[PDB]
Image: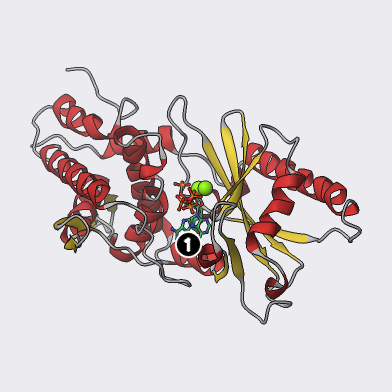
Amino acid sequence: MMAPVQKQFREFHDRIKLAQYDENQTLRDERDAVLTAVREGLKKVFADRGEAAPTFTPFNQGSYAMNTGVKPLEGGEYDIDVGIILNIAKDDHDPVEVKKWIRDALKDYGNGAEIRRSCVTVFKPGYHVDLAVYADPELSGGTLCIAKGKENSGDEHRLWQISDPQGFQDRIASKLSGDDAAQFRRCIRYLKRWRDFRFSSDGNAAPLGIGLTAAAYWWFQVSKRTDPVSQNVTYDDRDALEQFVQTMLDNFHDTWDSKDQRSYPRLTVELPVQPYNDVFEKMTGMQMESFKSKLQALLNALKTAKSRLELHDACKALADHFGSEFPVPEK
Ligand SMILES: Nc1ncnc2c1ncn2[C@@H]1O[C@H](COP(=O)(O)OP(=O)(O)OP(=O)(O)O)[C@@H](O)[C@H]1O
Ligand SMILES: Nc1ncnc2c1ncn2[C@@H]1O[C@H](COP(=O)(O)OP(=O)(O)OP(=O)(O)O)[C@@H](O)[C@H]1O
Ligand SMILES: [Mg+2]
Ligand SMILES: [Mg+2]
């Protein structure tokens, strides 16, 4: 019979997983260090304006909130995502200015902050902290809005955009339960490691993380077998990946670009909560074309790894796409 690869996938998962905030004191302390720095820095920033400093409530975001986090490859960075809800009315402030408050509060913290379009990012050895900045729903008419725009942006691109990070997190947590949900999370992690191994450490692959998470929300399906007599359950991560990758490939659509006078294959993945935006929208057509090609190569490898006699060969085919922490037994 063909060599199975489930034990190797579970070993691979053990190597790449990074514990979520609730189980990771190091991440909680690094998060809280950035949060304490912003409180102190705001004291100083606003004593300088004759105004009382604003208060904020933080909340966990991203993969370390959703338990979909992976360890970076050597040289890569961890990504601590957090939301802060300032006690301010959105109609009374420009979003970029509010993010300036936060950046200035984190001037002399670590490697200094940086105002990015959707967050303030502070850099420290081996990780960065992505602070998404929101206005208070109570003071802003009932809705939760994130500060969009950077110092580069014109008036068209400075806005307070409706956002539902807790509804998104709830949907990821609630789609499945128990060991079904564990396999869902494993497969998200496997594809994040594939991202880090086969796409560059620049931001062209920056939307892959959230994109693959939202893709899995729409399209992942469990693969397990239940013995009709013993009721014993075994999971098949290789097959779950094969079905999911094939479904992603099925949803690419050839999309004409009038500027370039050609089509590019594009995968649109809507966020399942507000603002329902295509989380892959920033990827260029040429990057989409490369993404599709690499997903197809991954799919071909997943199929090859089903049909090898030797476990070494099945695992080698997988490690060509998942990298050198995918275990490959000797022949
Ligand atoms: N393009 C986007 N559209 C909507 N929400 C987004 C988008 N990008 C990020 N987010 C929100 O911000 C959170 C943090 O974004 P990030 O890019 O760090 O993804 P992640 O889920 O943490 O995955 P990774 O492990 O790759 O960091 C996301 O989980 C999501 O809630
Ligand atoms: N709705 C969102 N909520 C929270 N974080 C987000 C959201 N959208 C994007 N991000 C995150 O913020 C970081 C950068 O934001 P963005 O995607 O705007 O890139 P940028 O380089 O700041 O802007 P751009 O690339 O458009 O010039 C990424 O990690 C991304 O995942
Ligand atoms: Mg993240
Ligand atoms: Mg991030």
The outermost residue toward the bottom is 141
Q: Secondary structure at mark 1?
A: helix
In the image, residue 182 lies at what x, y percent? 40, 52
Identify which residue is drawn at 56% across, 58% down. Answer: 149
In the image, residue 224 lies at what x, y percent? 25, 55
Q: Which residue is mark 1?
A: 173
Task: Inspect this view and state whether residue 88 appears.
Answer: yes
Examine the image and state in which quarter residue 144 appears.
Answer: bottom right
Label 1: few (<14), some (14–19) or many (≥20) C-alpha neighbours in 10 Å? some
Query: Is the N terminus in the top left, top right, bottom left or bottom right quadrant?
Result: top left
Q: Is residue 298 left or right of residue 193?
A: left
Q: Amino acid at mark 1?
A: Ala
Identify which residue is drawn at 18% across, 56% down. Answer: 265
In the image, residue 306 lies at what x, y percent? 13, 40
In the image, residue 85 lies at what x, y percent? 69, 63
Q: How is the image coloured?
A: secondary structure
Q: Is residue 161 left or right of residue 11?
A: right
Seen in the picture, residue 139 relative to 33 is either above or below; the reply is below
